[PDB]
Length: 130
Image 1 (cartoon, one colour):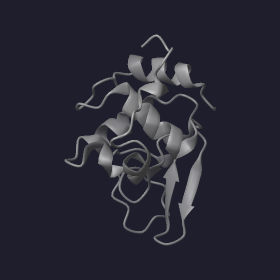
Image 2: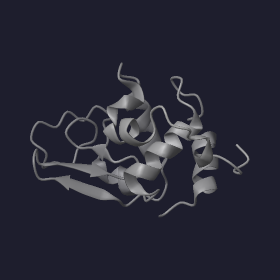
Image 3: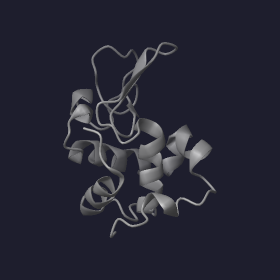
């Protein structure tokens, strides 16, 4: 599914993301925008290290979900990577919460540092009633 912006914002709020480990809803929205365009079916293969990024947060198969064909996979979310291509994002959010429980937090995604860190991100939640 491709979420609309305020639909996603209200879904992430209800799933407990606002302020999780100190990260505002507008930062999560900026991360999802630049990672996938709010598309749950996004996948990106990294030819370089043979891993794939899945779903709305583009979570990688070397460390977080298992796809069976990533060498050096760890599966820290204890999830099949196909659970990150569902239209329902509850499992994607459970795993994104696991990623930011490591010391790096949201910086784990370089897209967040390039497009969201030290920028005005208020625009992503404006008008959504969150």
